[PDB]
Amino acid sequence: PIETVPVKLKPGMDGPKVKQWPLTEEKIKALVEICTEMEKEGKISKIGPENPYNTPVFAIKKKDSTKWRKLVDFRELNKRTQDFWEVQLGIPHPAGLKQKKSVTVLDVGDAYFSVPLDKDFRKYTAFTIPSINNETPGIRYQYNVLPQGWKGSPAIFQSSMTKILEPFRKQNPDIVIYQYMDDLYVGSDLEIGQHRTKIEELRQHLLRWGGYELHPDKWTVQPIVLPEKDSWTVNDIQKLVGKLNWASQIYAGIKVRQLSKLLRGTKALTEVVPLTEEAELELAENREILKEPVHGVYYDPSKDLIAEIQKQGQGQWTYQIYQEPFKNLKTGKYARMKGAHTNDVKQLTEAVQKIATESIVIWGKTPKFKLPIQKETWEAWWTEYWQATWIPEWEFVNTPPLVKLWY
Amino acid sequence: SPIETVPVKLKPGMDGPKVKQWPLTEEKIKALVEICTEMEKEGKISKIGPENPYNTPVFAIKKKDSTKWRKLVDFRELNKRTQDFWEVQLGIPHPAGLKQKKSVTVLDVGDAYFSVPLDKDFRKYTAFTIPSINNETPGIRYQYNVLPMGWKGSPAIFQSSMTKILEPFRKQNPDIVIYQYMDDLYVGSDLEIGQHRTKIEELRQHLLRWGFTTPDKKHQKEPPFLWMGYELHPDKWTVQPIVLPEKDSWTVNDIQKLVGKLNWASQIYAGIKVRQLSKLLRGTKALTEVVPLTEEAELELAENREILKEPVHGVYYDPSKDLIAEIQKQGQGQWTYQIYQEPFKNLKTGKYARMKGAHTNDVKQLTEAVQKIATESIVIWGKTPKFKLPIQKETWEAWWTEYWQATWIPEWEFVNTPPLVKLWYQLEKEPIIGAETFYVDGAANRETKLGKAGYVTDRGRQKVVPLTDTTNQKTELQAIHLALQDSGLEVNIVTDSQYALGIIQAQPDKSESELVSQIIEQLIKKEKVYLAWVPAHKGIGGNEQVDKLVS
DNA sequence: TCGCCCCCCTTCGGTGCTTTGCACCGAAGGGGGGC
Ligand SMILES: C=C1[C@H](COP(=O)(O)OP(=O)(O)OP(=O)(O)O)[C@@H](O)C[C@@H]1n1cnc2c(=O)nc(N)[nH]c21
Ligand SMILES: OC[C@H]1O[C@@](CO)(O[C@H]2O[C@H](CO)[C@@H](O)[C@H](O)[C@H]2O)[C@@H](O)[C@@H]1O
Ligand SMILES: [Mg+2]
């Protein structure tokens, strides 16, 4: 019973037309049970094929909350949706979030279902539930309310969210709240138990009008390391020179003329070559240029974030986040702790959620990922491990590791 | 009939079609006048006049019955101007996805599209004029009041209508399985035959109130049921008979037909192969070009012919048992698989033979096969099977720890069915003590076409070969080829080509490139090879010297 | 002389790279099958 906010696509762009991929039995059953109730409650309506748009649908379970959560992959719809920096409905990002001891993520997407969506925009939200062995044609719905996963919903609901949170933030001025899509990121410098208690006060505050625990305090940077030995092969020095030559695209004033000269001639790779005093000075020089962060690298909010990941083995994953090439805003090392150690695709899917989560905390948005995996291998399995209510942009790269740069 | 109409639009800024009708005859347009008089009496079509400015041509073909005719209108022009639709048919039901049912019925709706009304505002665009007599006089004109056969919106709007009509019966009868494919209804239940038939009568009556007849001619009550190109027996299912062309002289188009039939056969006939027959299609230039069968293609064809003469059947799905998928390697990037739950009782078979990428290996293609089967299993049964794979656990372990991209296979157990999938060589992680060290380099001139490949070694050996009609990347591969050719069973190679290192490090065992194939063959014969990279033009080590020389 | 759907095999053409050809990938040609 609210006036709708008029919404448009970007000029010269049509709505999404993305095919539904196959779903397992239990995801299909969960979706039909979820969508039947949503239909009864008027949140979605059954539509026909004269609607030419579609967006893929699937479902996830977070391991702590074992009820299914419907997830519509509105990435295509969001790229074509008008920006809301123009209607002054965008959300600023608080720089204090990343300096908190603990940050808890809450899924508040259900709040959107109380605000209707522009009559003329709902056709762009259509999705299709598949059927096992194609017993029936797909079943089609569209939204009548602000959907979960649509970039417009936090923008339109924002004035409402501010009002609901104003008392809590008033009473807790040192707690930091940042909304990103369907999520609230809740940071505090408080001991673990009392943090969780104010989390629950938060919760009941929300429930009244209408938890996954981070420690950014303990994210670290993993710089480039140069091996340390006392005897050095020709092969070691070749490996060392190629690494430093690459790092000179990133760091300033890194030299290889002293180490390179040690390799005059055509030598056996296993020949041990003693280091001249000068070469030892050049390497100690290089070593501590790599010690400390690069000078001249600043976040630009008008450019996209990009993330690269390299598989390093034994469950270790290195990553860099940047906007311009070789100007890394962050370099890191993800390591999983599940002990099972068996699944590359699961580890990479979890590495992606963690990296994207860090970017949300730090900069307020997720990066576009360059994924070290075949397209078809990622697409066979990734939804089995996804636990976020958002989905980042990604693309698939096959880049062999020339130097083992980041490990 | 009393269904609510589905509103439809032309694409923005577009008008309706304005073409002309064809070959204009006494026989043809008196047959035309007869054809439509009964449709008009049914209300399916209405006479129109010249203030309707649109037109489209019409024709007819024979039905599967093959005394009946099928009215068709060449709506190609109208279709391009009609709004797009989101198609609700997402796939094709498969008999291996059916569970055993106590009582089964197959029904079909009569004159299905003609029972669904067309948007009143859109009808004027379906105009077809049937001329007067061989273009003497003004001409007879009709428009559709119902879904036309040939219009791109018709199948979607029919399916959507059929779904709405069935919905009350489905929710009311959730223990009755109804496969709905276009106007074809498979109905299975675990009720006794007498109750089953009572539920069918109810369903037929419900369809009839909504204007969908179910004529007795297409009402199947007894096995074997003819369904979706198959025969459904109580315990098993067969494909309807596949007849392969038996030409003495083969055109390209003949070969294309044959490969298609074999692919269709491969869903239940194990071990079908089409690589050699498909090879004959490459580089050809006309569908009527005669193509002589190679010896390999004749052998492949004879092998499949043997397979096809044996009768086969699939069984039905039992949800309380596991799905199992077993894969065998057939050579030249061909794979074949069977899916079963009890041994020697296949639900279905299949094959994977796609060549993805210029350079690859058997482990990657096995991984691809696994992914194809995983996708199809989810489509058909809603879950992934357990895999039986002809690859050792050590081999797989060796692969996913060295290979830099993330990769994975779900729960699988080794099955010893040679030939097994294996890595054919593995690059050393450290330089080999006592092995010669080759510094290789190749360069080509972009304009020239001309290049050089050569090496320089720590044992004083050196060599340069001139190359014509080459590229920069080829001379680098060529340089590596040369070192492998001239070196012992253990060798250390240092290149400045990220490109060449990239291909070789992925351990390919096959390639569309003859040069890369030769390198692979050389790598397989070596005992140990360490391959290292250095940046070019940095005056490094032996790299500078070999660089020196190919200039 | 038609429509819509799935599948496979081949060919073509757009994209982006610290490239100058190469690898990747989507679309469209042919075929099979369904209604
Ligand atoms: C699936 C379809 C319905 C049921 O297919 P159907 O074989 O049962 O035909 P229908 O029920 O009408 O007559 P019936 O009384 O003998 O059952 C038909 O309406 C129309 C559609 N269809 C089928 N084939 C063709 C075709 O080639 N070209 C076109 N444009 N459309 C076709
Ligand atoms: O993985 C790419 C694959 O996913 C689809 C959805 O089926 O596209 C999604 O992912 C892309 C990569 O970020 C987005 O650009 C796109 O908007 C989103 O729908 C397929 O389109 C694509 O093949
Ligand atoms: Mg029919």
Image (cartoon, coloured by chain):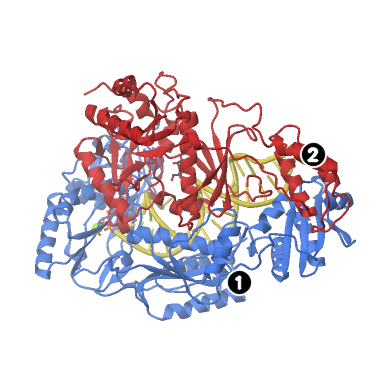
Chain colours: A red, B blue, C yellow
In the image, what residue occupies the spot 27% across and 29% down? A206
Quick one: SS at disc 1?
loop
* Residue B469, placed above or below residue B99: above
Looking at numbered disc 2 in the image, what kind of residue is underneath it? Glu
Task: Say if residue A393 shows up in the picture.
Answer: no
Place of residue B118 in the rendered image (x, y in percent of width and height, measured from the top left):
25, 41
* Residue B242, placed above or below residue A308: below
Q: The numbered mark 1 sits on a residue in which chain?
A: B
Question: Looking at this view, is A242 or B137 the one in front?
Answer: A242
Place of residue A67 in the rendered image (x, y in percent of width and height, measured from the top left):
28, 47
Tell me the tag on residue B292: 1
Q: Which residue is mark 2?
A: A282
Looking at numbered disc 1 in the image, what kind of residue is underneath it? Pro
Q: Cβ(mark 2) to ligand 2 < 8 Å?
A: no
Q: Cβ(mark 1) to ligand 1 < 8 Å?
A: no
Quarter location, residue A115:
top left
In the image, what residue occupies the spot 13% across and 61% down? B200
Quarter location, residue A120:
top left
Q: The numbered mark 2 sits on a residue in which chain?
A: A
Quick one: SS at disc 2?
helix
Quarter location, residue B92:
bottom left
Tell me the tag on residue B5: none
Place of residue B393 in the rendered image (x, y in percent of width and height, measured from the top left):
52, 68
